[PDB]
Image (cartoon, rainbow, N blue to C red):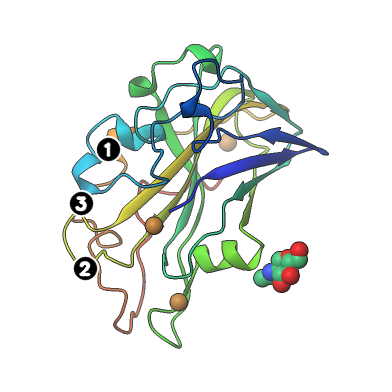
């Protein structure tokens, strides 16, 4: 359980969608982060992979604002403290808004994977995962925006998938967090995108999995990584 509190880009903080504060107001502030109804700080499990909830989390609506990023710039997402028990991959996608991200229909977004990190070491099962890297970085993840993609407005869908209960069907816990970015530069690629509801299926080998045994490999879920 947790969420993204803050986003650091080019020397300033962009406050996140504070899901334990803003839902409790009739008049919440405008931010670059999508609003959600996930006030339990919880997740979307396999029962929701083909519902709109998987796209940007439960009940999500686009943020009003969009943050510019320098070409090949970094975006640092700062989480609430991630539990070590919640071992799993950290995955990053972009989907073009083809216009203002604040007015997109999320069900039409087509995401391409820009980064993925999974099982890092398995000397002591359940092992060390991307989630553990996130914890070791004081609950932060740094995403680099590719220089090779077409500039424009994009949703960044940043996600941890916790696997501590994933040995049962629908036991994996997805924690997607979306923010609006203005990607800048000279790139030209428009990578093939995957609908949010076609990212994951509840029997995928990286989703329905027993992490407590020795693992010879880990197939990070979702569509293929865009490599340039
Ligand atoms: C894994 C890690 O380095 N965690 C550090 C912690 O040791 C340190 O006390 C804190 C200071 O703000 O920053 C964080
Ligand atoms: Cu949890
Ligand atoms: Cu562990
Ligand atoms: Cu190219």
Q: Mark 2 sits on what residue?
A: 167
> Which sits earlier in the primary sequence, circle 2 or circle 1?
2
Residue 145 visible at all: no
* Nearest-to-viewer mark from 2 and 1: 2
Q: Residue at x 18, y 56 (%)?
A: 203
Q: Mark 1 sits on what residue?
A: 198
Q: Which mark is residue 202?
A: 3
Alpha-carbon distance for marks 1 and 3? 11 Å
Report x, y in % for residue 159: 46, 47
Residue nearest the observer in this picture, 27 or 122? 27
Report x, y in % for residue 179: 56, 31
On screen, residue 191 versus residue 180, left or right, reads: left
Alpha-carbon distance for marks 2 and 1? 21 Å
Report which quarter residue 1 is drawn in. bottom left
Relative to 59, is 97 above or below?
above
Q: Residue at x 56, y 44 (%)?
A: 4
Alpha-carbon distance for marks 2 and 3? 11 Å
Report x, y in % for residue 184: 71, 26
């Amino acid at each position: 359980h947790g969420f993204v509190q803050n986003i650091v880009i080019d020397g300033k903080n962009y406050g996140g969608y504070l899901v334990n504060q803003y839902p409790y107001m009739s008049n919440p502030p405008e931010v670059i982060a999508w609003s959600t109804t996930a006030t339990d700080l919880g997740f979307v499990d396999g029962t929701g992979y083909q519902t709109p909830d998987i796209i940007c989390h439960r009940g999500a609506k686009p943020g009003a604002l969009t943050a510019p990023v320098s070409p090949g710039g970094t975006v640092e997402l700062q989480w609430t403290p991630w539990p070590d028990s919640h071992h799993g991959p950290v995955i990053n996608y972009l989907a073009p808004c083809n216009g203002d991200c604040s007015t997109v229909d999320k069900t039409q977004l087509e995401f391409f994977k820009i980064a993925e990190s999974g099982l890092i070491n398995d000397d002591n099962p359940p092992g060390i995962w991307a989630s553990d890297n996130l914890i070791a970085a004081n609950n932060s993840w740094t995403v680099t925006i590719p220089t090779t993609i077409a500039p424009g407005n994009y949703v960044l869908r940043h996600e941890i998938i916790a696997l501590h209960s994933a040995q049962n069907q629908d036991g994996a816990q997805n924690y997607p967090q979306c923010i609006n970015l203005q990607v800048t530069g000279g790139g030209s690629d428009n990578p093939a995108g995957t609908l949010g509801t076609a990212l994951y299926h509840d029997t995928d080998p990286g989703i329905l999995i027993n992490i407590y045994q020795k693992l010879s490999s880990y197939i990070i879920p979702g569509p293929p990584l865009y490599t340039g």
